[PDB]
Structures are given as C-alpha cells and as structure tokens.
C-alpha cells in the first residue's frame, strides 16, 4: 500500500505449486529478495472458479529484474509445497484470474 491500484506494466510472474492456504505475506517471504510493484498491490491468487483457492497465483513484480529475482527460485519450496515461478505478462494474467466471474 504505496503504489496502485494495480498495473506493474508487464512484470507478472505466475506462481504454481504453492500451499492451499497461502497469501501475499508468503509471496513476499518466499521473495524476501524482492520488491513487487508496491509490496502487495501486484499479487493475486487463483481460484478453482466456484468457491476455493488453488496452489496457483500471479504477481506483478516491481521491475523485470524483480521478475528475474523470482526466476532464481523457479522450482524451490515454501511450506511442504513447491513454488515454480513462470515469467508472465498482465495481458495473460487479466485473462487467467478474471474467469471465476464476468
């Protein structure tokens, strides 16, 4: 809560493998290396589309060198659970989130 509402131009990273109950405080802890385009006003979680979260997410980083900092970890773990990090863009992310609804 320093920049927003959203719009990290293209520095999205997709996040896959993650715990079924995790949140941005864990994105920011897994990437204590890293900025994000605000801190939390670039993170989103994915949702099975009807009434639950999933082990998947997407995060507008605070530069593409933040994206690269997240790629350093691209098959690590945080929890008893894996954290694959794909390099993404807002143009994909706006599709993949916005399909649990209108």
Image (spheres, helix red, strand yellow):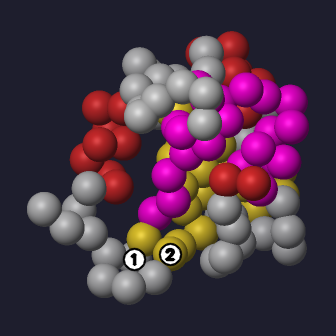
> Dot 1 lies on which element?
loop
Comparing 99 with 37, the one in front is 37
Q: Is residue 98 left or right of residue 93?
A: left
- Residue 58, percent across and down? 51, 47
Q: Is residue 65 above or below residue 23?
A: above
- Residue 35, percent across and down? 73, 26
The magenta region covers 26-46
Q: Residue 61, can we see it?
A: no
Residue 72 image-quadrant placement: top right
User: Residue at 53% of width from left, 73% of height from top?
Assistant: 54
- Residue 33, percent across and down? 86, 30
Tell whether position 36 is magenta. yes
Residue 23 image-quadrant placement: bottom right
> Dot 2 lies on which element?
strand
User: Residue at 67% of width from left, 76% of height from top?
Assistant: 21
Decide: few, some or many residues near mark 2? Use Cα within 10 Å; few <14, some 14-19, many ≥20.
some
Screen quadrant of the C terminus:
bottom left
Decide: few, some or many residues near mark 1? Use Cα within 10 Å; few <14, some 14-19, many ≥20.
few
Q: Residue 54, can we see it?
A: yes
Q: Which residue is mark 2?
A: 53
Q: Which residue is mark 1?
A: 48
Screen quadrant of the N terminus:
top right
């Amino acid at each position: 809560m320093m920049l927003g509402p959203e719009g990290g131009e293209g520095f999205v990273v997709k996040l896959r493998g993650l715990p079924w109950s995790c949140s941005v405080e864990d994105v920011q802890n897994f990437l204590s290396d890293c900025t994000i385009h605000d801190g939390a006003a670039g993170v989103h979680f994915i949702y099975t589309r009807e009434g639950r979260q999933s082990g998947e997410a997407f995060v507008e980083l605070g530069s593409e060198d933040d994206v690269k900092m997240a790629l350093k970890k691209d098959r690590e773990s945080m929890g008893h659970r894996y954290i694959e990090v794909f390099k993404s863009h807002r143009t994909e992310m706006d599709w993949v989130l916005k399909h649990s609804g209108p």
